Length: 137
Length: 137
Image (cartoon, rainbow over all chains, first blue to last red; front, side, top):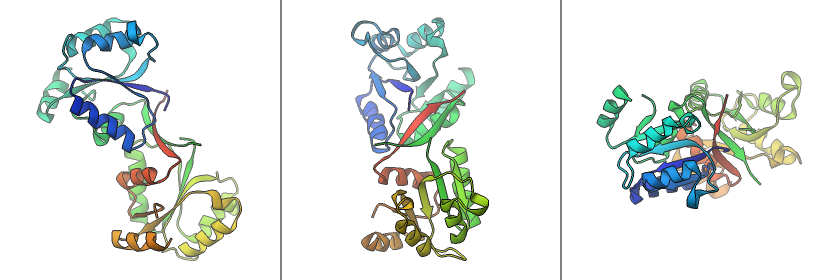
């Protein structure tokens, strides 16, 4: 449970689905949320209010973002020699759109919302990620 | 992923379902299997062929066991001042039987087979167990 997860999603309903999924199914991975692209880059660069953010080990990225787009966030990520290494899953709004997105992006795409099932599929699609059951005090 | 899991189940079809679930969904927890009660106690006591077995952190126990029953295994477990501390989930064959089993055993019961969904519910029902996503080389 070392790696923190950064969810860049503007929909409060959809953020709620992921929060409750992590909660009800006992995911220990710290879930962090940015509601627009400008806040997402503030988190990654660890600037401003996020001056003490942890580096995420997984970024989950919607494309519909106010203030700064999903595309801008991804483009600024892959420019940075450090942020480029971080795994990115792009949220699509429809499995049909998901077929289109993989054709031209393939595993780094899942349809939203990210409930626990979809999050389990994310973990499956990403080679270096694994589930473990940990006992705790 | 420190804790090993001991599955005491005689059905090869049902053992197959759990093996593939752990495999396809990338559970790192070592899964160990005993096909009857006598082998299960051989594992716990770490005797004979299992002289170097690891202590399990979770035991999943069918009641239909040849050679030595599910009840015998549980009774010998709770006698032992060491083995008694280990979490035990009892497999029932029907959610109806599961309602009966909890009335008189409540969370330590799930209907078989143990696919990944049911295993996730086991983890939910057991206070000190948590899921974590771990990155790996």
